[PDB]
Amino acid sequence: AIFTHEGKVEGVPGNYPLTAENLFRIGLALCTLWILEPTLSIPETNFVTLALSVGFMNAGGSVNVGGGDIKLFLQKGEIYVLEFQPLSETDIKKLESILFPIPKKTGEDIGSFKC
Amino acid sequence: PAIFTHEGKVEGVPGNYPLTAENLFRIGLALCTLWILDKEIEEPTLSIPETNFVTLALSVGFMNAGGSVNVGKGGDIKLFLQKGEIYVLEFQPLSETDIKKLESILFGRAPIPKKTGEDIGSFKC
């Protein structure tokens, strides 16, 4: 599954649910969930946070590292454990319904990224 | 089966093929793969000029194949980007024979191997 019962998305970077494709869609849906521009704050730049960022931007949201509408907490250990704030069990259900064709923006409608 | 213009560049509207997130991911994956296999550089590096949807989508693919990226300069391969309505991507060093090799990988039905875990590259702002 994408989200644990505790409400987190975890795994080994590169393996589902942390594939570039799925992380990209998680990001698309997160921005969409907030629109239906939004801003995501990530703690660091790595494969996982960046794949999530590209999707968030593709949907018209902007991301920064240092904090906006949604903030990502990440703990890198045996596995990666991601937590979004704020995201209730309701937000998570809304998300799950979107992920399971999420529209995308193009050209200048695409969000930005700031280191 | 090609994306490079007769001028040795890739052009398009961000979000529209060949500049979709999916395709850019694949371009990044293929570029890194080309450097590891053809140039025999085990951990190639890509330098991007700035951070936006196109350069980052490209970076994710590059890292997924085992390469590392930095914003600035110094890498084995460096990206030159012209923005605007139609983005224009140029890589250096990328010869015409390199472009053919790259496209062969991009349009090939053969899967482009992906690395995982500790083997995925890093990103430096």
Image (cartoon, coloured by chain):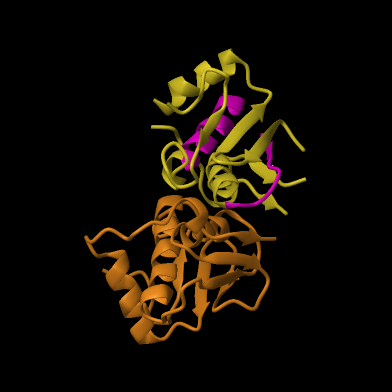
Chain colours: A yellow, B orange
Magenta span includes A34:
yes
Taking the spot 44% from the left edge, 52% from the top edge, the residue there is: B116
Coordinates of residue B98 in the picture (x, y in percent): 37, 82
Magenta span includes A48:
no
**Relative to residue B7, is residue A31 depicted above or below?**
above
Taking the spot 41% from the left edge, 38% from the top edge, the residue there is: A16
Coordinates of residue A24 in the picture (x, y in percent): 48, 42
Q: Residue furthest right?
A: A66
Taking the spot 43% from the left edge, 53% from the top edge, the residue there is: B16
Q: Quadrant of the N terminus of chain A?
A: top left
Q: Residue furthest left?
A: B109
Coordinates of residue B22 in the picture (x, y in percent): 41, 51
Q: Nearer the viewer, residue A115 or B2?
A: A115
Residue B105 appears in the figure: yes
**Relative to residue B10, is residue A14 depicted above or below?**
above
**Relative to residue B116, is residue A32 depicted above or below?**
above
Q: Residue furthest top?
A: A90
Residue A104 appears in the figure: no
Taking the spot 56% from the left edge, 56% from the top edge, the residue there is: B56
Read off the magenta span.
A23-46
- Using residue A114 as the reference point, say whether residue B2 is left or right of it: left
Coordinates of residue A74 in the picture (x, y in percent): 65, 38
Q: Quadrant of the C terminus of chain A?
A: bottom right
